[PDB]
Structure formats: C-alpha cells, structure tokens
Image (cartoon, rainbow, N blue to C red; front, side):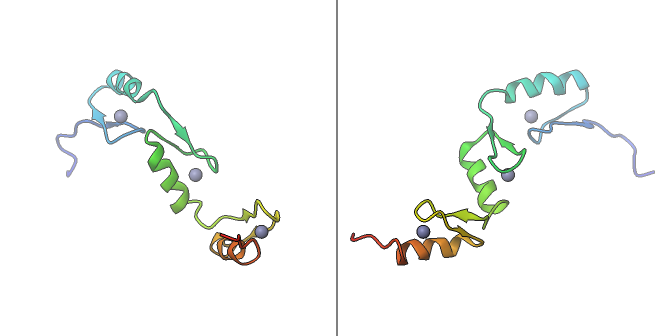
Length: 92
Ligand SMILES: [Zn+2]
Ligand SMILES: [Zn+2]
Ligand SMILES: [Zn+2]
C-alpha cells in the first residue's frame, strides 16, 4: 500500500522538527527551552515575543476592551478607539 518506507514519524510540538527516534525528540525539545512567551488570553505559547502579539491580534482579535478612562467596555475595540478621540479628546 501507499505506506511503504516511512520515516521521521516523531514530530516536534514546538517546531517543524522531526526524527526517527523518541529520545532525539526529547533532547531536541531541550534546545527550544529558554524564552517562552505565553498568551495572556489562552494556554498559547511562543518563542518569539513579536509573534505572540500577533497571535492575539489574529486569535483574540476584537475582544471586549475596557476603556482605561471611563471603565467602559466595548464589544469591538475599533469603536473604543474612536470613543476616546471623541469623549476623551485631548487638547493636543
Ligand atoms: Zn523543535
Ligand atoms: Zn491566545
Ligand atoms: Zn472612555
């Protein structure tokens, strides 16, 4: 059948790494260790801080935002922005 000569079945849940041995997968994961930026919305994690931010702008995008000025929640942040410029419109 299709499945003939398979290899590198073990995949890394941290990156697109692979190996033909479990042990290897373990030692390989050790390298990933270090800086782990977890999401402040879900059980998500990333090595690149810059990326983590995007995860929220793509996953948790348009989340109930609470105005730090009038403690007013807004279904769509987009609006919250205009609001501040409307009600909380600065002199500058
Ligand atoms: Zn890896
Ligand atoms: Zn998240
Ligand atoms: Zn406000």
